[PDB]
Image (tube, rainbow, N blue to C red):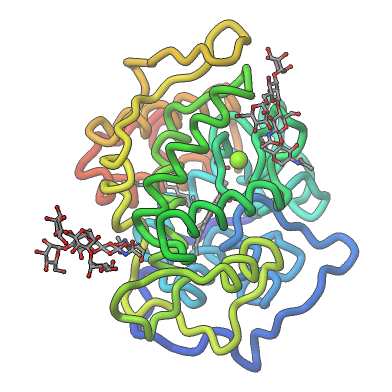
Length: 335
Ligand SMILES: *[C@@H]1O[C@H](CO)[C@@H](O[C@@H]2O[C@H](CO)[C@@H](O[C@@H]3O[C@H](CO[C@H]4O[C@H](CO[C@H]5O[C@H](CO)[C@@H](O)[C@H](O)[C@@H]5O)[C@@H](O)[C@H](O[C@H]5O[C@H](CO)[C@@H](O)[C@H](O)[C@@H]5O)[C@@H]4O)[C@@H](O)[C@H](O[C@H]4O[C@H](CO)[C@@H](O)[C@H](O)[C@@H]4O)[C@@H]3O)[C@H](O)[C@H]2NC(C)=O)[C@H](O)[C@H]1NC(C)=O
Ligand SMILES: *[C@@H]1O[C@H](CO)[C@@H](O[C@@H]2O[C@H](CO)[C@@H](O[C@@H]3O[C@H](CO[C@H]4O[C@H](CO)[C@@H](O)[C@H](O)[C@@H]4O)[C@@H](O)[C@H](O[C@H]4O[C@H](CO)[C@@H](O)[C@H](O)[C@@H]4O)[C@@H]3O)[C@H](O)[C@H]2NC(C)=O)[C@H](O)[C@H]1NC(C)=O
Ligand code: HEM
Ligand SMILES: CCCCCCCCCCCCCC
Ligand SMILES: [Mg+2]
């Protein structure tokens, strides 16, 4: 049993704006067994049928869906998708849950690997999210109205009632402070440190209608529609160019910050980690993740070994471009 995993799709042929909330991709409510998780992007694509509506998909489906639905840039899609798949997907069946555990991903892999989906805390998903609560408080996937209220507040205080790059700079810092003060297990290093800055500009670059060319800013009605209800705005047109994390540099600049966490199970006790990846040391992220994959798969032998080798190579093709050159690692050798 098992699947032979194809290489990732390339960029879409057509890269302009278009109506994505169309007749063939209607919003529909969740059925029994349907899965949703911490990503509002993937959630919206599933609830409109760009992904399978049950929220379980192949890497290739996820990549084509983020491109068709949102014009997410090809390399960015590769980096995110195979990261999620290596850590949280089933490499043998080639299926990833965008939320929690489900029989739909197929017969479970050998522990410590889990294939328990994007909900799994610790190596990918982490703390100081915009509309999701830290895992320490008991739920890392659900929309949180109190946190959305803070999104609205900061938009009112810094963005004239809209979400824009200024708001993102301020909100990111403030959420870090919230977690320092209230979460003794707060971690903000490695994958999370990098992903946390990119996530704060995705709403600007990808959730703002593509026909808006100037003074791009997101309304709270549209924010609520996507973040809470998993629904495209009416007549939503995607970005007119492939995009991802443009502006993330500026968000960090507004309140410079260093990877680390609360030490010794205590609040207000943030200690820097000088070994973590950061924005001038991106290849460390690659090495760390390959490390984590070795911990999940200490001695694979069969179809599982084959599919690990392929998925690792696929990921590297994206990482190499995105991080400006990394030496490929071969922890399971060549095919
Ligand atoms: C996200 O969204 C938010 C919200 O919309 C958005 O915020 C806007 O940000 C821009 C900046 O990018 C703001 O525009 C700038 O505002 C600067 C501050 O203006 C104040 O001070 C001015 C300077 O006063 C001089 O003169 C007085 C004498 O009167 C003197 O005492 C002072 O010492 C000083 O020397 C002042 O003119 C201005 O007041 C005018 O405007 C207000 C309306 O806002 C009006 O009520 C007043 O009566 C008066 O007409 C104000 O109090 C300002 O310095 C800056 O100007 C520079 O650029 C212009 C060119 O655009 C040049 O002409 C000039 O030489 C300056 O170099 C500019 O106007 C804007 O106001 C924000 N809007 C809000 C609501 O906050 C973010 O940008 C968004 N983020 C992203 C990434 O898009
Ligand atoms: C949606 O998301 C929000 C935000 O994450 C959740 O609300 C948080 O819930 C946690 C857990 O109950 C709260 O944590 C506690 O906060 C105390 C500080 O509170 C004051 O200061 C903050 C920050 O300025 C204010 O927002 C707040 O109103 C108070 O004025 C801490 O002192 C507590 O620490 C104690 O427990 C920890 C853990 O055991 C120990 O390590 C400490 O030493 C100490 O004994 C604690 O951390 C947090 O304040 C809440 N925030 C907000 C904004 O309400 C919601 O629960 C969530 N909703 C759902 C349904 O999930
Ligand atoms: C390409 C595959 C994708 C994967 C695997 C993925 C995965 C994730 C994960 C795991 C999180 C949670 C992060 C955390 O708490 O640390 C997340 C959050 C997020 N994703 Fe995605 N994502 C993908 C694509 C997209 C796309 C295309 C968009 C935008 C259109 C998007 C927008 C977001 C936003 C805004 C958040 C933050 C939600 C919040 O903090 O409240 N993602 N994603
Ligand atoms: C947050 C939703 C998508 C996940 C982002 C994962 C990307 C990891 C690194 C991105 C590259 C940053 C510098 C080019
Ligand atoms: Mg989170």
